[PDB]
Amino acid sequence: CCSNPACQVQHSDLC
Image (cartoon, rainbow, N blue to C red; front, side):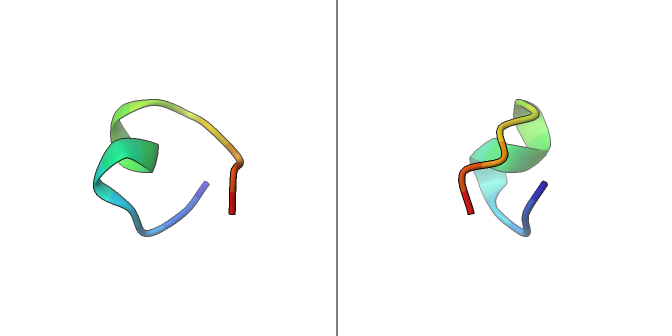
């Protein structure tokens, strides 16, 4: 989903 620490943990297409 993104190259973030949280994104990797939880699939969240925020970017």
